Amino acid sequence: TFNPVYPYDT
Amino acid sequence: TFNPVYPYDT
Amino acid sequence: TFNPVYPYDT
Amino acid sequence: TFNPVYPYDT
Amino acid sequence: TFNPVYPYDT
Amino acid sequence: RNSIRYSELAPLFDTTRVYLVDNKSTDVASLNYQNDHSNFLTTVIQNNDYSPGEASTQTINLDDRSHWGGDLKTILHTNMPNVNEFMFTNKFKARVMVSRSLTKDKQVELKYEWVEFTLPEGNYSETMTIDLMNNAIVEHYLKVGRQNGVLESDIGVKFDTRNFRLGFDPVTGLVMPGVYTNEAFHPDIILLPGCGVDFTHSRLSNLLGIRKRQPFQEGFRITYDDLEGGNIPALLDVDAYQASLKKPVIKPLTEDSKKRSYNLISNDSTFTQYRSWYLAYNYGDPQTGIRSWTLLCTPDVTCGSEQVYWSLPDMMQDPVTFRSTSQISNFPVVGAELLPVHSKSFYNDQAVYSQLIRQFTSLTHVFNRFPENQILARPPAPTITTVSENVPALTDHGTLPLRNSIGGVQRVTITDARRRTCPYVYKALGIVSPRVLSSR
Amino acid sequence: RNSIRYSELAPLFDTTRVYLVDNKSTDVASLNYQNDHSNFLTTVIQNNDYSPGEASTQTINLDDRSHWGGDLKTILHTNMPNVNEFMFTNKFKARVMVSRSLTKDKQVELKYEWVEFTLPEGNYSETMTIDLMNNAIVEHYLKVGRQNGVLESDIGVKFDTRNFRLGFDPVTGLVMPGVYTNEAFHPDIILLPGCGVDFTHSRLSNLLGIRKRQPFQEGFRITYDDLEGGNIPALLDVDAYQASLKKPVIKPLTEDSKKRSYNLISNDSTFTQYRSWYLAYNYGDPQTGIRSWTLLCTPDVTCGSEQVYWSLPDMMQDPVTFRSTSQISNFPVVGAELLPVHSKSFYNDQAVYSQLIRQFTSLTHVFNRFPENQILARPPAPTITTVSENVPALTDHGTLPLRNSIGGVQRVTITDARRRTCPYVYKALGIVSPRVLSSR
Amino acid sequence: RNSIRYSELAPLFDTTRVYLVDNKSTDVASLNYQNDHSNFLTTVIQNNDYSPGEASTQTINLDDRSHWGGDLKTILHTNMPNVNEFMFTNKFKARVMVSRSLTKDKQVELKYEWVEFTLPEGNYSETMTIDLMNNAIVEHYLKVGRQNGVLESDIGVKFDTRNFRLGFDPVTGLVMPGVYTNEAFHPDIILLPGCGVDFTHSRLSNLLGIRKRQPFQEGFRITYDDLEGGNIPALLDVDAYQASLKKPVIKPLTEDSKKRSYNLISNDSTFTQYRSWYLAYNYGDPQTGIRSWTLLCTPDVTCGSEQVYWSLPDMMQDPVTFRSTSQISNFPVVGAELLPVHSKSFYNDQAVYSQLIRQFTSLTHVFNRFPENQILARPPAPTITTVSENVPALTDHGTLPLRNSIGGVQRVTITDARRRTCPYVYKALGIVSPRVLSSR
Amino acid sequence: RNSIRYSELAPLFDTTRVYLVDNKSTDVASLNYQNDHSNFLTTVIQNNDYSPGEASTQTINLDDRSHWGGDLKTILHTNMPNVNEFMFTNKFKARVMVSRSLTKDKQVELKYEWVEFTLPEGNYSETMTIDLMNNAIVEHYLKVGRQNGVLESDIGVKFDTRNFRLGFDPVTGLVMPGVYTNEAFHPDIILLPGCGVDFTHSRLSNLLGIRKRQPFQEGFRITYDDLEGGNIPALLDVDAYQASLKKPVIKPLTEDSKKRSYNLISNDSTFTQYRSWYLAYNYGDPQTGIRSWTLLCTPDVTCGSEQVYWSLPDMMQDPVTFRSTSQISNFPVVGAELLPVHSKSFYNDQAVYSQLIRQFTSLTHVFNRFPENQILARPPAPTITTVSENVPALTDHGTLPLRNSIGGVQRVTITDARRRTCPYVYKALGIVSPRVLSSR
C-alpha cells in the first residue's frame, strides 16, 4: 500500500 | 452515417 | 517516345 | 594492479 | 605502383 | 532668471529631473486602481512626507520669466499576442458551403453563406496560425456542413502555402509526379466555386502576406470568381501510366484513397475546380488577373507595425494644433513611437520532416484530418518561421515645451492608432529633464 | 571664470572627467568591505600618492562663480536569475487537496488547504519553470497527499500549456481523437473542484502570461469557481467505437492504463470536472467569464522588466523634489534605467519530439510521473523557448547639476523599484564630465 | 520673435511637433484613395473639428521674422519580396538549345536561341532561388527542347554551387572518387558549348554572387566562350578500375545510369565539354580568364542594398539644387535611407543531409529530375542559408529648413533609386519638430 | 551673412543637403565607366536640366563671409569574401617534403622545400577553410610527393584542431584510449621533422587564431624546430593490452590499418615525431617554448578587422596635415570606418556527428583521404562555426570643413589600409549637410 508515484514500467 | 472526419487508420 | 523527364523509379 | 581509469567495455 | 590516395574501401 | 522652485526646499537652477512612474507604492494604493499601465496617474512629487493627493496640491515651478522645455525619453514595454481580439487578428470572414441537397426531382441545390470564424487568442508563429484558420473552417463544417449534405470533397476555402504547379507539364496538362510537390513557398488561399474569403475587418490578411495595391479603399474581398486563370491543375494517374507500360497519361487522378473527388471541371479537362491565389498572381493574366490589384508580400506575423501615441496633458504644452480637452481619447499627443513588437526569424529544416514527425509528436492528426487528399492535406511548414516577440523599447522623444507650473499629479496616457488605451502595456515610465529655451 | 582646481595641481578649465569606479585596489581593501556592487564607496581622487581616506579630505572644486553640471553615462552589468527569492519568482501559493476520507458512516470528507511551494533558484527557461512548478505540487502530495487518502486521480492544480479542445466535436461532445492533441499553445492552469492558485505575492504570474486587466488592485487569486464555462471535455473511447464497427461513441473514456479516473461530472456528461484557464478565456462567456478580468499575454521569462534607480548623494544636486538624507533607501535619484535582462528566443522543433527523447535522455520520468493520464501528463514543450539573459548596459543619463565641491570619496548606489540594494550587480561604474551652465 | 501661431489658439513658442501620418481615419476616407503608403496626403492639422480639406485651408505659421528648420525622424516599414518583378529579380535571360536535328544527309544541326525565363514572385532563400532558376531552364526544355530533338544529355546552362575539381588528380586527369564531391562552396553557372546567360536586366546576378569588376559598363553577358580554361574534368570509371585489379584508370566514365552522355570533348581527353564559372575564376588564367573582369563575391539575397528618397514638397524648403515641381517623380529630396531589408543568416547542417531527406519530405524530385547525372544533379544545399527579411527602420534625418507657412495638407512621398513610388511600403510616417535658426 | 546660392535659383539659408550618390542614371552613362563603387564621380547638381559635365561647370556656393562645415554620414555596403586574393587570405607558404630517396648505397636522402599553396576564393566558414588548406597540402603531394618517393606516412604539415593529449597517462606514456580523443578545441598546426609553415604574407594566420606576441616584427615563420617539447604522444596498443589479459601496455601502436607508420622517434619512446603547436603552447616550457612568443587567440574568420578611409577631395578641406594632391592613392582622408564584415556564430552539435554523416552526404572522402591514420585523419568540426558576413554600415562621421565653392562634380573615394580602391564595394553614398561655423 505504498505509491512510489513513478511508472517503473517504461 | 456519421463522419468523424478523422483518419483513425494511421 | 515521350520523355516525362522524371525518374519514377526512386 | 593498474587502474587505467577508463571503461574499455563500452 | 600508383597511389590514388583515396580509401575506395569505405 | 532660470530658477526651479518647490514648496520649501532650496531653489535649483538650470535643470533637473521629474519622474513619471507607475510603480510607486503609495499612489497605486490610492490614485490609480481602476486604471492600467496606459492610463494612470502618478505623483511627480517624490517627497517621502506628504500624503499623495495632498501632494497633488503642491507644484513644481519652473521660473516664470522663461519658456521652458523638457527632454522626454521613455521606457515602454508590452507583451501583446500575435493573435488577439483587440488588434483584430482573431477573426476573419469567409464564405463556405452550408448545404448540399437533392431537390425538386433533378436539381443539385448548393447553398453558400458568409460566416465569421474566430481564433483562440495567443497562438503565435505564422504557420500554426494558418493551421488554426484552416481548422476553424473545419470546426464549422463539423457543426453545419456534414449535417446538411456537403461532403469533405467539396469544402470551400482552405489556406495552403505551396505552388500547385511545380510538377506541371505543358503538354500533358498534368502534374506528372502524381503529387503536388510538397514544399512551402508562400501562403495563399484556395477556393472552390461559389465561395471565398473577406478580411475587411482583419489584419490576418497582412499575416498571409496578401495586400491591396490600393490600401485606402476599405474592402478586402477575394472571391472565387476573382482568382481567374489559375485553377490548380490535376495529378497524373502515376499508377495507371506506369503499370500501362499509346500510354494512359491523359488519365488525371479523379479521387484518392478514401475516395474523395478532386472536383474536376469536366470528364475531359486536366484542370480542377480548385482555384489558388498564388497561381493567379504569377501564373494568370498580369493585366486583368489578381496581380492587377493585390500584392504578393512578405508575411510578417505582427500583422502590421502599428504606432502608439503618448500624452502628458498636465505637463507639456499642447503641440501646435491640438486643443486641450479632458476626453482621454483626444488628449494632445507629444510623442509617437512604434508599438514594441518584432519579427524574430528562425530556421527549422525540421519543417515537413517535422510535419511528418510533428504528427506523431502531437498524438492527433487534428490539423491534417485529410492526409490523402492532395489539396485538403496539411500545408507544408515553411523553413523560416516567424514569431511576434515583445521587446522593451528605450525610445527618445525630443525636448517639448513645459508648463511653468507642474502639478503634483500628472496623468500619463499611451494610446493607439485609433485612440484608445492599449491593454497590453506592462511597463511605461518616462524621465523629463527641463531646461530653459528663451525668456518673456 | 570657469576653473576646476585640485589641491596643488595646475588648474584645469572648461571640463574634464571624474571617475566613479568600484575596482580600485586600494579602496576595496579599506573602504567598502561589508558593502557590495550596489552600495559602495570609491575615491574620485585618482592620485597615486595619498592614503585613501586621507584622500577623503581633499576635494575637487568646480569654480564657484558658476553653476556646474555633468554628463553621467554609466556601465551597469548584472547576472540575476530567472527564478530567485529576491525578485519574488521562487514562491507561489496554490490550494490543493490535503485529505480524502471515509467519514461518519456514509460521508466523503474532502479537506483542502492553501500552501506555498518554493522553487530552487536559477532554473531558467519557461517550460522548465512550469515543470518545476508542477513538480512542487507533486513533491507536496508526496509529503501529505497520499498519506492522508487523496489519490493521484484527484490532484488539484496543474500548469499545462495546451488547448484541451482541439479534437472536440460539436455533436459527440468529445475529443474524437481519444487524445488531447499534444501541441503547446500557451501556458494555462488547470484546476479540480474546490482548489485553485494565488499569485498575490509572485511574479511567476507574469511568466505564465496571465495578467489582471486591472493591475493595481493587489490580489491575484484564480479559483476553480472562476474558471466557469470551460471544463476540459472528455475523450472518445477510441477503442470501443472502432472495435464496435448504433455506434458506441457516447462512450467517454473514464480512466486509462493504470486506472486513474478522469473525474467526470456524472455518468452522463461528456465534460470532466477538470477546468482550464485557457478555455475559459476564449471558449467561455466573454462578458462574465474570466476573459472579463484577466488578459492573455505573451509569456516573458524575466517575469517583468523592472527598473533600477541610481544615486550619487555626494556628487549631484538633489533633483527637484527629493530631499537630502542619509537613509540609503531614500537617497535622491539621478537616473533611472531598466534592469539589464532580456528575453532571448530560440527554436527547438526538438520540443515534444525531445520531450519524447528528453525523457530517455534524462534517466527519469521525474516530471512525467503520470505518462498515461491525458491530463496529469507532462505538458508539451512549446517551440520557441525563452530564457532570461543578462547583458551589460551602456546607458546614458543626461547632464545633471553638480556640487561645486566634490568630496574625495563619493558614495554610489543602485536601488530597485522598492528601494533596496540589488544583490545581483556584478559591475557598476560611471563617468562624469562636468561643464558650465550659467553663473552666480 | 519666435512664435508659432495657428488659426485661433494660444500662440506657442520655440518649438513643437507636426505629425505626418497615413493612418488617420478621416483623410484615408476622403483624401488618399487611389494612393498608397508611398505617395499620400495627410492633414497636419490634428484638430478634431474641421472637415479635412476645410482643414486644408488652415495653416501652421512659424513666426515670419525667423528662418525655421525642423528635425525629421521617420519610421519606415516595408515587406518586399526577395524575388519580385518591380525590383528586377524575377527574370533573367539565358541562351539554351532549342533544336537538335539530323540534316542534309550527314550534318548535325544545332540551333540555339536566347530566351527570358521568369520566376514566381516571393520564394526567398538563396539556394531555393537557384533551384527555381534551374527549374525554369527545364520548364522551358519541356515546352520546346525535347519536342525538337535536344536530349537531356545536352541541356545548356545550369546553376550549381560546387567545386567540380575537388577529386581531381594531376596525373590521372580525372576526379578519382568517381563522383563530383557533393559539397557546396559558392554559386556558379555551368555552360555547354554554344550557350550562356545574360543578366543585363536583372539583380539575380548579385544573388549568385558574381559581379563585374567594372559595374558601370551596362552589359552583363557571360558566354560559354568566356569560361575559357576550366571545363569540368571527368569522372574516373571507379567500377572498371577496381574490378580490374596495367590498370583501366584512363577510363573516364562516359555516361551513367539511364545512359546520359557527359559530352566529353573527344574519345581521348579527360575533360568534358561542360564549362564552370567557378573554375575559370580561380583555376583558369588569372590574366586573361574570367577572373580578369568579374569578381567572386558573397551572395546576399536582398540582391542589392538599394536606397529610397523622401520628399515633403509642401513642408520643407527645396535642398540646394533641386528645383520645385509638381512631377511626383522629381520632387525635391530631403532624406535618403537604405530600403529596410536585411540578410539573416542561418545554419542548416541539415543541408544535403536534408536535400537527401528533403527529396522524400517533398513528395517529388521536381528539382532533382536527373538524380544520376553528376552534373544535372541537384546542387548541394550550402550550410548557412540567407533570407531577405523585412525590418522596421527607425531612421533619423537631420534638421531641414521649413517654410514659414505650413499647409493644412502635406504630401508625403517615398521614392526609389529610379524615382518611382515603391509598392512594398506598409507603413511610413514622420515626426517634425521645428525650431529657430536665425532671423530676417 | 550665411546664404547658400546656386546658379539662378532662390537663395537658401542656414543649411541644406548635397547628395553624393553613384546610382544616378545620367552620370553612370557618361562620367564613371572605367571606375567602380570605390572611386567614382558624381554630380552634386541634382537639377534635371543641364547635361552632366555642363553641370560640372556650375557650383554650389556657401556664403563667402563664413567658414562652413558639413555633417557627413555615409552608407557603405560591401560583400567581400572570407577568403580572397586581394585581402591576402588565399595563399600561404609552408615547407613540405618533396623527395624520399635511396642514395649512395646506404643513405636515406630527404629533400624538403618551401612552396606556396593557394585557395579557391570565397569558401567561408573556418573549419572548411582549414580543410581547404589541408587539401592544398595534399593536392601538392599528388603532383610532386608520391612521384618522388615520399609516402603518405611522412606528409609534413597538417592543420588539425584537437588536443592530442587528452587520453595521455603520466605513467604509461601513452594515450590509453588507443585513439586521439576526437573532439575539437582550437586550431593548431602539426609538423614533421624538417618542415613547417610561414604566414609572413597571409592573414590566414589570424584565422587559425595564432598571433605573434610582437606583431610589428614582420616575419611569421613557425618551424618544426620551434615546436619544442610537445610532440604528439603515441597510442596504446588497445588490442594487444586487452587480448593479453605483466601486461603488454608499453606497446605503442606503430601503424594502423592500411599500414602507415606513426613515425615514432625510436623503438623505445612513447612519443611520435609529430609535433603540435597547441601542445607546445600550454604543455611545453612556458619560459622558452612557443608560448613565449606567440599567442593563443580566438579564431575570427574575417581574418582581421581592417579599416577603410573616405575622401572627398573636391568638397572637404584637407584635414590638418594632409596635403592636397591628385594621386588617388594619397587623397586627404576625412573619415575612417571599419570595413563592413562581422563574425556570425552558430551551433552545429551536428559537427563530428556530421563529419561522420557529412562524409556520406558528400559523395567523397576528399578531405578525409586517410580515415585510419589518427593524425592525418580529418580534424573534428568544432561546435560553433564562424562565418564572415557582410553587412551594410550606417556610419556617421563628424562635421567637416567645406570649401565655399562646391564643384558640380565631386569625386568620392574609399580606400583601404594600404591605400587602394577596394573592389568589394557594392554601394557607397553619403549625405552632407552644411552649416555655418564662424566668419571671416
Image (cartoon, coloured by chain):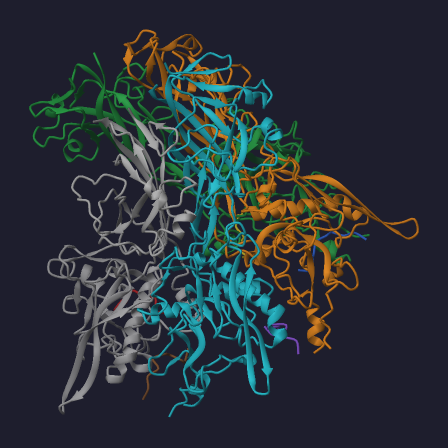
Chain colours: A yellow, B blue, C purple, D red, E brown, F orange, G green, H cyan
The residue furthest right is F105
The answer, for residue F389, to whether it is visible in the render is no
Question: Residue H345 at x, y = what percent?
Answer: 42, 52
Decide if residue F306 is on the left or right side of residue H287.
right
Examine the rendering and report whether any part of residue G238 can be seen: yes
H209 in relation to F205, above or below: below
Q: In this orientation, which residue lies closer to the viewer: H349 or H322?
A: H322
Residue G317, how many percent across, how many down? 26, 18
Number of on-image labels: 0
* Residue G346 horizontal/vertical position (percent): 45, 47
Residue F20 image offset from top left, x and y in percent: 41, 21
Q: Quadrant of the C terminus of chain F?
A: top left
Whether residue H323 sits left or right of residue F166 in the image: it is left
> Does G10 sit above or below residue C6?
above
In the image, residue G74 sits, relative to residue F104, either above or below, namely above
Picture layout, residue H348 above or below residue H260:
above
Lateral position of residue F349 relative to residue F365, left or right: left
User: In the rendered image, which quarter is residue F357 located in?
Assistant: bottom right
In depth, the one of G253 and G202 nearer the eye is G202
Q: Which part of the image, by quadrant, shows the N terminus of chain F?
A: top left
Q: Nearer the viewer, residue F202 or H64?
A: H64
When asked about the image quadrant of residue H431, the answer is top left
